[PDB]
Amino acid sequence: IVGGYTCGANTVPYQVSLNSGYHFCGGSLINSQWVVSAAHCYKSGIQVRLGEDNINVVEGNEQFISASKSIVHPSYNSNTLNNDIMLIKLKSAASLNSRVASISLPTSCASAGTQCLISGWGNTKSSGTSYPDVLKCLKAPILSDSSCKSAYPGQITSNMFCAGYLEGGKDSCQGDSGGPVVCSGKLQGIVSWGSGCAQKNKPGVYTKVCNYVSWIKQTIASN
Ligand SMILES: N=C(N)c1ccc(/C=N/OCC(=O)O)cc1
Ligand SMILES: [Ca+2]
């Protein structure tokens, strides 16, 4: 997260870290057994880490649970990043408490102009590289679809939305991939892609979770 702020320990209790020997992506806990992340975060041997603040120090509130299965969206296209969503099932149910909690799926799509909370342990520089210890947060508005399409001509599908600041300076970044965009207490987006980070006229592009609720519900009812 570039140009954001330190969230505060366990104030984003649905935020997870995906670990494969190292942190590589974020995710969102949607119930005791399932995490929503980006399909571009897919790999084998994922361990889900819940209740994290400092990802490099065991502070006492963590739950580390291996993934039992990963389910990439059936229409995910890794070239265009259309349908950039994946479900990850935990080998055992997480213990839900104040520091580990699920985030609601949306019943309707979010509105242009709505300020959302984006979070992660990704790069904090728009140029150069610095990775934070503790979880970072960013408040950013959903942009109009016309401004989104103008920023990325020929690249924005109906399964994507833009959020952030056209002036640049504030954005999600590498390492935040798969993490939450929460608007009005609902998981509305997943950190997907963008040209660089915090670049002028290049806002963040996010998977439009409201389009996937049926698929999510069907998949979790059957796996
Ligand atoms: N909001 C952005 N500008 C943005 C969002 C997501 C990415 C994803 N990078 O994937 C590689 C990785 O995470 O290691 C890049 C830029
Ligand atoms: Ca920790």
Image: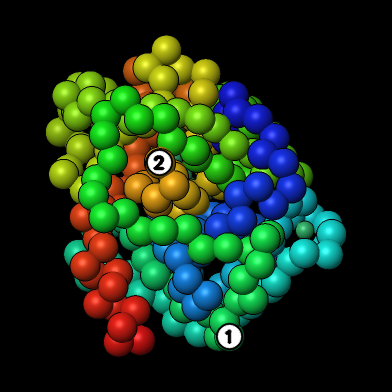
Above or below residue 219? Residue 105 is above
Q: Which residue is mark 2?
A: 183
Answer whether residue 25 is visible to the viewer in this image: no
What kind of residue is marked 1?
Ser
Name the secondary structure under disc 1: loop
Residue 118: assigned label: none
Structural distance between the alpha carbons of marks 2 and 1: 28 Å
Image position of 178 (left or right of 9): left
The local crowd at label 2, few if under 14, some if 14 to 19, many if 20 or more residues have their Cα within 10 Å, is many
Residue 26 in the image: x percent, y percent?
54, 55
Does any atom of ligand 1 lie closer than 8 Å to the CB of label 2? no
Here the colouring is rainbow
What kind of residue is marked 2?
Cys
Residue 14 in the image: x percent, y percent?
55, 58
Q: Quadrant of residue 110?
A: top left
Q: Earlier in the sequence, mark 2 or mark 1?
A: 1
Q: Which residue is mark 1?
A: 92
Image position of 189 (left or right of 94): left
